[PDB]
């Protein structure tokens, strides 16, 4: 189901090329969305059963713990070695802003035939990595889209991307592997705390070969070369239509919740 | 006069009867086919000659667009050739002006058309740009009239008629005009002003527009706005290179026509004006 979900064909071999191919296909096939937290449905269970059920069988997307959770289990089953890492999102944050919570989950992946480790992150939303990169401080690393770079200060790593010119820090992380329960505590926080960006509004995102799409409330942003594109939807009806048809999210397991009404309340949050 | 060339330019064919159904079809075909654009004035090339020969050579033979005098000029000659009776009218653009702002210059030209088989006259205007009329409407003050897009309304005070459009729920006055028919030379004096005065909107920046069944497209400098049913899009081009690509490939305008003028360098000066 997963391979089909992402449009790949059989069982691929556990090597570096496969990692590049699964990331690409994951990127364009499973959207980032927070419809469950938006509707008061916690993301509490990060088991394989729960994640496969939601992101594969029911054709929903999810946020970082759901995406990277799922990819983690997929890659393990193919024969990669996978450690789950946690980090703090520093994107666009004022210098001297307080230390952010650990709200992001990424993968450190070891690949038979390769020597070190790879940062894999398909769950960061509209600016997520679209290639695995080497878990190596220093070099500017090319991806399918913009250049990225890791730096290191002690045991803290920062991922930065060169976005429309500028070098922007995205998040910091340590390479300490996390047990699933510690990820579940963080996911409980991100999906239920009243000040979470994922509780107060709607975020949907996906990445094709040519563009990064990012929807917040009524505002769809599209980033491609030479141009930034901003679509403002008139009402919740158009936003749902974009959720279902543009972003490919199946709303069937949410039957009996007033999705449109909730979306209407968060068009401008 | 090359009637068949014009009809071909606008995606039509045959020779239609001079009736109301034909007036609607030619307006909708012109709206989607011949863009609003001011490249000539932007590049210091005046729009001075409003003869049928000049407007046909530019807007039909050369696959350029133009601004109001050129559009409604061309359409006016086509419409007489088909057997409509046509008067050219001038007006003053009031779109978004303060209540206290000085009287505007007469910088807009529209058509008042008698249609065989219909009572009264029709206002026809394919030349106002992205918010131009997409149907002929009855030149009748009072009622709200439907078009292929938004409701529009004419009101009257003295010898001034105001055209307003209901734009996303809000009534906006576009321009005022009188029904005094204008000779070509009065239009030409107006077009001279609009295409050469250093404070003209069409001299200090770039405006490109086209209207399809589903959307109004409006480009000012680097910003492309698209109004569709249920959404607006705002595309911001990074530089003049992307703006030219839009002009050529999205709006279908042939720039080979302006060779030797460095279009890109001039558009690079007006991305934000
Ligand atoms: N779960 N957290 C996330 O998905 C996330 C948090 C912050 N920024 C992008 C993504
Ligand atoms: N010639 N004038 C025009 O083309 C025009 C003037 C004002 N607003 C839109 C279009």
Image (spheres, coloured by chain):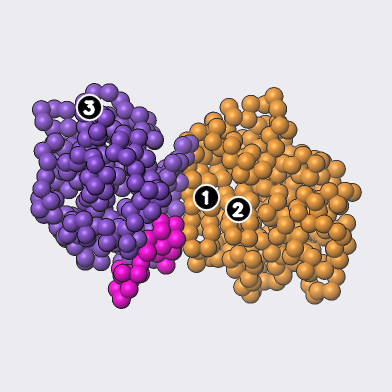
Chain colours: A purple, B orange
Chain of the residue under the numbered disc 3 shown in the image: A
Closer-to-camera residue (B271/A86): A86
- Spatial CA span between label 2 and label 3: 59 Å
Q: Earlier in the sequence, mark 1 or mark 2?
A: 2
Indicate which disc residue B225 carries.
1
The kind of secondary structure the magenta stretch mainly shows is helix
Closest to the camera, between mark 1 and mark 3, is 3
Residue for point 10% across, 48% down: A179
- Residue B12 visible to the viewer: yes
Classify residue A172 by image quadrant.
Answer: top left
Q: How many other residues sit within 10 Å of disc 1, few (<14), some (14-19) or many (≥20)?
A: many
Decide whether residue A238 is among the magenta residues: yes
Q: Secondary structure at mark 1?
A: strand
- Spatial CA span between label 1 and label 3: 51 Å
Residue for point 24% across, 41% down: A79
Q: Secondary structure at mark 2?
A: loop
Marks 1 and 2: same chain? yes
Q: Secondary structure at mark 3?
A: loop
Decide whether residue A51 is among the magenta residues: no
Q: Which residue is mark 3?
A: A115
Whether A13 is drawn above or below B145: the answer is above
Where are the magenta residues, as a range? A237-262
Residue for point 63% across, 44% down: B251
């Amino acid at each position: 189901g997963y391979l089909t979900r992402i449009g790949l064909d059989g069982r691929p071999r556990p090597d570096l090329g496969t990692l590049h191919a699964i990331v690409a296909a994951h990127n364009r096939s499973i959207p980032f969305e927070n419809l469950d937290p938006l509707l008061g449905i916690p993301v509490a269970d990060l088991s394989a059963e729960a994640l496969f059920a939601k992101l594969v069988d029911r054709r929903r997307g999810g946020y970082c713990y759901e995406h990277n959770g799922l990819l983690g289990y997929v890659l393990e089953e193919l024969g990669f070695e996978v450690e789950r890492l946690s980090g703090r999102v520093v994107w666009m944050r004022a210098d001297d802003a307080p230390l952010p919570a650990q709200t992001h989950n990424v993968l450190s992946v070891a690949v038979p035939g390769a020597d070190g480790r790879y940062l894999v992150d398909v769950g960061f939303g509209g600016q997520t990595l679209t290639s695995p990169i080497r878990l190596e401080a220093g070099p500017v690393q090319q991806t399918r889209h913009e250049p990225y770079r890791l730096t290191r200060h002690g045991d803290d790593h920062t991922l930065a991307a060169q976005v429309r010119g500028e070098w922007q820090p995205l998040y910091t992380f340590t390479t300490e592997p996390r047990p699933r329960i510690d990820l579940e505590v963080g996911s409980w926080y991100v999906s239920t705390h009243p000040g979470s960006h994922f509780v107060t509004g709607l975020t949907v995102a996906v990445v094709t070969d040519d563009a990064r799409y990012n929807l917040r409330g009524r505002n769809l942003a599209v980033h491609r070369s030479g141009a930034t594109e901003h679509i403002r939807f008139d009402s919740a009806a158009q936003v749902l239509d974009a959720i279902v048809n543009r972003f490919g999210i199946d709303l069937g397991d949410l039957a009996g919740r007033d999705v449109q009404a909730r979306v209407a309340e968060v068009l401008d949050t």
